[PDB]
Amino acid sequence: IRMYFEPGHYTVMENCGEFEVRVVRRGDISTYASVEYETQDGTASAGTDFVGRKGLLSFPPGVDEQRFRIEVIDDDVFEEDECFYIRLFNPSEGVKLAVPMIATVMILDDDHAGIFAFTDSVFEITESVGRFELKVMRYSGARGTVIVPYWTENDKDYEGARGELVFENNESEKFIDLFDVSFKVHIGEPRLAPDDELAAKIKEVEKKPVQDLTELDRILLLSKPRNGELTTAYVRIR
Ligand SMILES: [Ca+2]
Ligand SMILES: [Ca+2]
Ligand SMILES: [Ca+2]
Ligand SMILES: [Ca+2]
Protein backbone atom coordinates (compact mmCIF):
# COMPACT_ATOMS: atom_id res chain seq x y z
CA ILE A 1 1.43 -3.47 -0.69
CA ARG A 2 0.00 0.00 0.00
CA MET A 3 0.92 3.68 -0.57
CA TYR A 4 -0.72 6.63 1.18
CA PHE A 5 -0.27 10.26 2.30
CA GLU A 6 1.07 11.16 5.74
CA PRO A 7 0.60 13.80 6.95
CA GLY A 8 -2.77 13.45 5.22
CA HIS A 9 -3.46 16.99 6.28
CA TYR A 10 -1.23 20.08 6.30
CA THR A 11 -2.13 23.51 7.59
CA VAL A 12 -0.10 26.30 6.06
CA MET A 13 0.49 30.07 6.30
CA GLU A 14 -0.14 31.95 3.06
CA ASN A 15 3.38 33.34 3.55
CA CYS A 16 5.12 29.96 4.14
CA GLY A 17 6.63 30.16 0.65
CA GLU A 18 5.94 26.45 0.32
CA PHE A 19 5.76 23.22 2.32
CA GLU A 20 6.35 19.48 2.24
CA VAL A 21 3.61 16.97 1.56
CA ARG A 22 4.78 13.55 2.69
CA VAL A 23 3.78 10.19 1.24
CA VAL A 24 4.26 6.68 2.64
CA ARG A 25 4.89 3.23 1.13
CA ARG A 26 3.66 0.28 3.26
CA GLY A 27 3.89 -3.39 2.24
CA ASP A 28 6.53 -4.76 -0.13
CA ILE A 29 9.28 -2.15 -0.20
CA SER A 30 12.02 -4.40 -1.71
CA THR A 31 11.28 -3.29 -5.29
CA TYR A 32 11.05 0.21 -6.82
CA ALA A 33 7.54 1.68 -6.64
CA SER A 34 6.00 5.03 -7.46
CA VAL A 35 2.79 6.99 -7.66
CA GLU A 36 1.52 10.28 -9.03
CA TYR A 37 0.02 13.32 -7.33
CA GLU A 38 -2.03 16.24 -8.66
CA THR A 39 -2.96 19.42 -6.80
CA GLN A 40 -6.59 20.20 -7.47
CA ASP A 41 -8.81 23.12 -6.53
CA GLY A 42 -11.06 23.54 -3.52
CA THR A 43 -12.07 26.99 -2.36
CA ALA A 44 -8.38 27.84 -2.78
CA SER A 45 -7.63 28.46 -6.44
CA ALA A 46 -4.62 27.03 -8.25
CA GLY A 47 -3.45 30.23 -9.85
CA THR A 48 -4.44 32.60 -7.05
CA ASP A 49 -3.79 30.68 -3.82
CA PHE A 50 -1.28 28.02 -4.80
CA VAL A 51 0.33 26.56 -7.93
CA GLY A 52 -0.98 23.49 -9.78
CA ARG A 53 1.28 20.41 -9.81
CA LYS A 54 1.15 16.86 -11.23
CA GLY A 55 4.19 14.82 -10.27
CA LEU A 56 5.85 11.45 -9.93
CA LEU A 57 6.80 10.16 -6.49
CA SER A 58 9.48 7.55 -7.12
CA PHE A 59 10.24 4.94 -4.46
CA PRO A 60 13.54 3.20 -5.12
CA PRO A 61 13.89 -0.22 -3.48
CA GLY A 62 14.11 0.45 0.26
CA VAL A 63 12.21 3.77 0.47
CA ASP A 64 8.73 4.03 2.00
CA GLU A 65 8.23 7.75 1.86
CA GLN A 66 8.62 10.71 -0.47
CA ARG A 67 7.91 14.32 0.36
CA PHE A 68 7.34 17.07 -2.23
CA ARG A 69 7.27 20.86 -2.20
CA ILE A 70 4.00 22.64 -2.84
CA GLU A 71 4.09 26.41 -3.34
CA VAL A 72 1.59 28.55 -1.47
CA ILE A 73 1.06 31.92 -3.19
CA ASP A 74 1.06 35.17 -1.18
CA ASP A 75 -0.83 38.43 -1.81
CA ASP A 76 -2.37 41.46 -0.04
CA VAL A 77 -6.04 40.81 -0.57
CA PHE A 78 -8.10 39.65 2.35
CA GLU A 79 -9.66 36.23 1.84
CA GLU A 80 -11.32 33.93 4.33
CA ASP A 81 -9.79 30.50 4.90
CA GLU A 82 -9.38 28.61 1.59
CA CYS A 83 -8.81 25.00 0.44
CA PHE A 84 -7.12 22.83 -2.13
CA TYR A 85 -6.08 19.18 -2.33
CA ILE A 86 -3.62 16.67 -3.71
CA ARG A 87 -4.61 13.24 -5.12
CA LEU A 88 -2.62 10.01 -5.59
CA PHE A 89 -3.18 8.17 -8.84
CA ASN A 90 -1.03 5.92 -11.06
CA PRO A 91 0.53 3.69 -8.38
CA SER A 92 3.19 1.33 -9.76
CA GLU A 93 2.12 -2.27 -10.39
CA GLY A 94 3.11 -3.98 -7.14
CA VAL A 95 0.79 -1.92 -4.99
CA LYS A 96 -2.66 -0.71 -3.87
CA LEU A 97 -3.77 2.84 -2.98
CA ALA A 98 -4.62 3.33 0.72
CA VAL A 99 -6.25 5.84 3.08
CA PRO A 100 -5.71 8.67 2.59
CA MET A 101 -4.72 9.06 -1.02
CA ILE A 102 -6.00 12.61 -1.04
CA ALA A 103 -4.00 15.11 1.08
CA THR A 104 -5.76 18.28 2.29
CA VAL A 105 -3.90 21.57 2.60
CA MET A 106 -5.58 24.76 3.84
CA ILE A 107 -4.36 28.30 3.18
CA LEU A 108 -4.64 30.78 6.06
CA ASP A 109 -4.80 34.40 4.99
CA ASP A 110 -2.81 37.03 6.82
CA ASP A 111 -4.30 40.12 5.17
CA HIS A 112 -6.66 41.12 7.98
CA ALA A 113 -6.49 44.58 9.54
CA GLY A 114 -7.36 43.32 12.14
CA ILE A 115 -8.77 42.86 15.68
CA PHE A 116 -7.66 45.17 18.50
CA ALA A 117 -7.73 44.74 22.31
CA PHE A 118 -5.87 45.04 25.64
CA THR A 119 -3.88 42.16 27.18
CA ASP A 120 -5.47 42.04 30.65
CA SER A 121 -8.04 44.18 32.50
CA VAL A 122 -6.10 45.16 35.62
CA PHE A 123 -2.56 46.35 36.23
CA GLU A 124 -1.30 46.98 39.74
CA ILE A 125 1.24 49.82 39.99
CA THR A 126 3.61 51.90 42.12
CA GLU A 127 2.59 55.07 44.06
CA SER A 128 4.81 57.33 41.89
CA VAL A 129 7.65 56.04 39.68
CA GLY A 130 6.92 57.88 36.44
CA ARG A 131 5.97 55.70 33.49
CA PHE A 132 5.27 52.72 32.20
CA GLU A 133 3.73 51.76 28.87
CA LEU A 134 0.21 50.38 28.42
CA LYS A 135 0.25 47.84 25.60
CA VAL A 136 -2.35 47.38 22.88
CA MET A 137 -2.25 44.17 20.84
CA ARG A 138 -3.40 43.68 17.21
CA TYR A 139 -4.64 40.14 16.57
CA SER A 140 -4.57 37.88 13.58
CA GLY A 141 -3.71 39.86 11.48
CA ALA A 142 -1.65 42.85 10.59
CA ARG A 143 -2.53 44.24 7.17
CA GLY A 144 -3.27 47.85 6.27
CA THR A 145 -2.85 50.90 8.47
CA VAL A 146 -5.32 51.20 11.32
CA ILE A 147 -5.93 54.27 13.43
CA VAL A 148 -7.50 53.92 16.84
CA PRO A 149 -8.49 56.51 19.48
CA TYR A 150 -7.49 56.32 23.16
CA TRP A 151 -8.76 58.15 26.24
CA THR A 152 -8.68 57.73 30.02
CA GLU A 153 -11.37 57.84 32.75
CA ASN A 154 -11.49 58.61 36.50
CA ASP A 155 -12.54 56.21 39.29
CA LYS A 156 -4.64 64.37 41.32
CA ASP A 157 -3.31 60.83 40.71
CA TYR A 158 -2.37 60.79 37.01
CA GLU A 159 -2.48 63.12 33.99
CA GLY A 160 -5.28 62.43 31.51
CA ALA A 161 -4.25 60.82 28.21
CA ARG A 162 -5.78 61.02 24.71
CA GLY A 163 -4.82 60.28 21.13
CA GLU A 164 -4.91 57.99 18.11
CA LEU A 165 -2.43 55.17 17.74
CA VAL A 166 -1.04 54.49 14.28
CA PHE A 167 -0.34 50.86 13.42
CA GLU A 168 1.45 50.82 10.06
CA ASN A 169 1.59 47.58 8.12
CA ASN A 170 2.85 44.64 10.21
CA GLU A 171 2.59 46.81 13.26
CA SER A 172 1.22 44.28 15.72
CA GLU A 173 1.87 46.16 19.00
CA LYS A 174 2.00 49.81 20.13
CA PHE A 175 2.02 51.59 23.49
CA ILE A 176 0.21 54.33 25.37
CA ASP A 177 2.62 56.25 27.58
CA LEU A 178 1.40 57.28 31.05
CA PHE A 179 1.83 59.63 32.85
CA ASP A 180 -4.90 51.71 46.31
CA VAL A 181 -6.89 53.84 43.84
CA SER A 182 -8.00 53.07 40.31
CA PHE A 183 -8.98 54.59 37.00
CA LYS A 184 -10.09 53.26 33.61
CA VAL A 185 -8.64 53.77 30.15
CA HIS A 186 -10.63 53.07 27.00
CA ILE A 187 -9.99 52.27 23.36
CA GLY A 188 -12.52 53.42 20.76
CA GLU A 189 -13.14 51.74 17.43
CA PRO A 190 -10.40 51.12 14.81
CA ARG A 191 -10.77 52.64 11.35
CA LEU A 192 -8.43 52.57 8.42
CA ALA A 193 -6.51 55.67 7.39
CA PRO A 194 -9.33 57.60 5.80
CA ASP A 195 -7.45 57.74 2.59
CA ASP A 196 -5.83 54.42 2.21
CA GLU A 197 -6.84 53.00 -1.09
CA LEU A 198 -8.62 50.19 0.63
CA ALA A 199 -10.81 52.42 2.81
CA ALA A 200 -12.22 53.75 -0.46
CA LYS A 201 -12.88 50.54 -2.39
CA ILE A 202 -14.69 49.36 0.74
CA LYS A 203 -16.65 52.61 0.89
CA GLU A 204 -17.62 51.76 -2.66
CA VAL A 205 -18.72 48.27 -1.80
CA GLU A 206 -20.43 49.72 1.23
CA LYS A 207 -23.25 51.23 -0.80
CA LYS A 208 -24.10 48.43 -3.16
CA PRO A 209 -27.09 47.16 -1.22
CA VAL A 210 -25.80 44.10 0.60
CA GLN A 211 -27.89 42.00 -1.77
CA ASP A 212 -25.60 43.31 -4.53
CA LEU A 213 -22.17 42.83 -2.97
CA THR A 214 -20.19 40.52 -5.16
CA GLU A 215 -18.88 37.60 -3.12
CA LEU A 216 -15.54 39.31 -3.49
CA ASP A 217 -17.10 42.49 -2.13
CA ARG A 218 -18.76 40.69 0.78
CA ILE A 219 -15.35 39.47 1.86
CA LEU A 220 -13.85 42.90 1.23
CA LEU A 221 -16.26 44.22 3.85
CA LEU A 222 -15.18 41.95 6.66
CA SER A 223 -11.55 42.81 5.96
CA LYS A 224 -12.23 45.84 8.17
CA PRO A 225 -10.59 46.24 11.63
CA ARG A 226 -12.70 45.36 14.68
CA ASN A 227 -12.58 45.32 18.47
CA GLY A 228 -12.23 42.51 21.00
CA GLU A 229 -13.94 41.73 24.30
CA LEU A 230 -11.99 44.00 26.66
CA THR A 231 -11.96 47.58 25.37
CA THR A 232 -11.27 48.97 28.84
CA ALA A 233 -8.50 48.67 31.44
CA TYR A 234 -8.49 49.63 35.13
CA VAL A 235 -5.28 50.90 36.67
CA ARG A 236 -4.87 50.23 40.39
CA ILE A 237 -2.48 52.57 42.13
CA ARG A 238 -1.23 51.56 45.57
CA1 LIG B 1 -8.49 32.98 -3.58
CA1 LIG C 1 -5.35 32.35 0.00
CA1 LIG D 1 -4.48 36.79 0.56
CA1 LIG E 1 -1.31 37.23 2.58
Image (tube, rainbow, N blue to C red):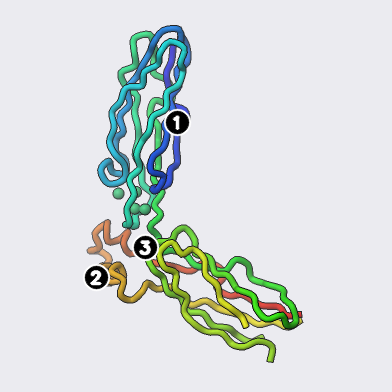
Which residue is pictured at 56% across the width and 76% down the height? 176
Which part of the image, by quadrant, shows the C terminus? bottom right
Label located before the other in sequence (2 or 3): 2
Three-letter residue code for mark 1: Gly
Which residue is pictured at 36% across the width and 46% down the height? 82
Q: Taking 53 as reference, is 94 above or below it?
A: above
Q: Nearer the viewer, residue 196 or 114?
A: 196
What x and y, as percent, mark residue 23?
43, 25
Q: Give the Cα separation between the discs numbered 3 and 1.
A: 31 Å
Left or right: where does residue 186 sit relative to residue 164?
right
Q: Give the Cα separation between the discs numbered 2 and 3.
A: 14 Å
Q: Taking 5 as reference, is 17 above or below it?
A: below
Mark 3 sits on what residue?
222
Mark 2 sits on what residue?
204
Mark 1 sits on what residue?
8
Quarter of image, res 218 = bottom left
Which residue is pictured at 31% across the width and 71% down the height? 196
Give the residue furthest to the bottom: 156
Left or right: where does residue 232 sit relative to residue 33?
right
Three-letter residue code for mark 3: Leu
Quick one: label 3, few (<14), some, or many (20+) residues within 10 Å? Answer: some
Helix, strand or loop at label 2? It is: helix
Mark 3 touches mark 1? (CB < 8 Å): no
Left or right: where does residue 134 sit relative to residue 194?
right
What x and y, as percent, mark residue 152?
58, 83
